[PDB]
Amino acid sequence: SLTQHLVITAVGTDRPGICNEVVRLVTQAGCNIIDSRIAMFGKEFTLLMLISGSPSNITRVETTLPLLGQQHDLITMMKRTSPHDHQTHAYTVEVYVESDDKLGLTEKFTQFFAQRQIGMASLSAQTISKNQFHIAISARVDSGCNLMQLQEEFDALCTALDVQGSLNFIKN
Amino acid sequence: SLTQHLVITAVGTDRPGICNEVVRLVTQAGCNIIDSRIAMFGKEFTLLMLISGSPSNITRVETTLPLLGQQHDLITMMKRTSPHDHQTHAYTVEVYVESDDKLGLTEKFTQFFAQRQIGMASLSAQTISNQFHIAISARVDSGCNLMQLQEEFDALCTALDVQGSLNFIKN
């Protein structure tokens, strides 16, 4: 059949089985779960998800999902999208930047990865207790990426912006 | 000054600098980005983000974020929450399950980990071409009895008669 893809976003007060019903409703709808991201932020359950199924099954998910969010104070958001081309990743680079000035610094580092077409998976930019600003980014690069070269360019940027930054590589 | 926390979630067509916009709007509003999850699913930019700031700044972001979205065809959702008890995990457990049946197999494994208070970071449950595979990346702190976890997990797979494995990775 014509396999259709859908993107799901959900936020709800984290409780024992909230994530059960979600994958329950999705899998029990005939759809496949291509990938997802689950994070516990604050007292909240946050989920990013990409599913695929027949046009019939997806609609089934597009209809039933909001109801689940009604009886659980859950908040949903969906959006159909083109199929997902699997980008296998060979490494996870973890970056850590520290500065005393936060002025437009974070977007300099996200741009660093965009210019190189490296997708980030997580980020944090914040002022710590006690007058410094710390940025933390996690990104995935494939096997075709020159690691020693990525590290050098990252060091140059850090020199250019006069901040302290470290880079870490982790393969899976 | 009475720190407020805001969970933000967005999904729009993946374009360049789209993420930059979000980070710019939030940081210029004087807020901190405590954590976030970014992913490119299909052809969409996907974001989960937890920010915090004073009520004035959070209100500012709550006010101007939707607008930014209207600009970049980005649909967003927001909700305030309580302080973040930032947990650290001693191990990352990669789980892999291979079966020749789809029927209610997924809930079994999520329940398995929810019941044991072991959080999941990612999940994929799909058929591959007549075998339904489940990949789960979960977090396990140091107070976990790895021997018991292994045994119970093996008993799960045995009861469902599927093939499962766990790979303990140190963070």
Image (cartoon, coloured by chain):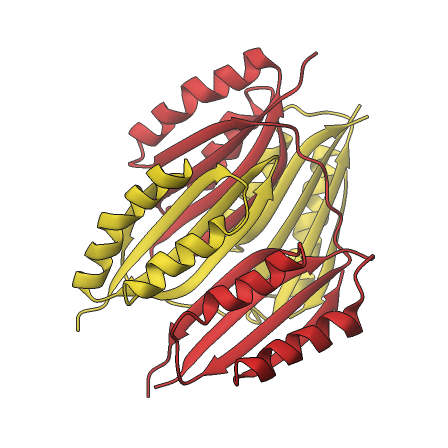
Chain colours: A red, B yellow
Q: Is residue B42 left or right of residue A20?
A: right
Spot occupied by residue A76 in the image (x, y as percentages of width and height): 38, 33
> Where does the N terminus of chain A fall, quadrant-wise?
top right
- Vertical placement of residue B108 versus A109, above or below: above
Task: Give how far across and how far down residue A139 sits, in percent.
Answer: 63, 61
Hey, which quadrant is residue A134 in on the image?
Answer: bottom left
| Res. A1 in view | yes
Residue B106's place in the image compared with A158, above or below, is above
Q: Which residue is drawn at 52% across and 30% down?
A: A24
Q: Where is residue A19 in the image (x, y as percent from the top left)?
A: 47, 40
- Residue in the picture at 46% in, 32% down: A21
A157 versus B31 height, above or below: below
Q: State the residue in front, A75 or B85.
A: A75
Q: Relative to residue A35, is residue A135 drawn left or right?
A: left
Q: Which residue is drawn at 45% across and 30% down?
A: A78
Along the viewing direction, whichever of A113 and B121 lies nearer the viewer: A113
Q: Which residue is drawn at the image coordinates 24% and 58% (left, top)?
A: B58
Where is residue A51 shown, x and y percent of the image? Answer: 59, 30
Residue B140 visible (yes or no): no
Quarter holding the C terminus of chain A is bottom right
Q: Along the horizontal axis of the image, is A2 left or right of A70? A: right
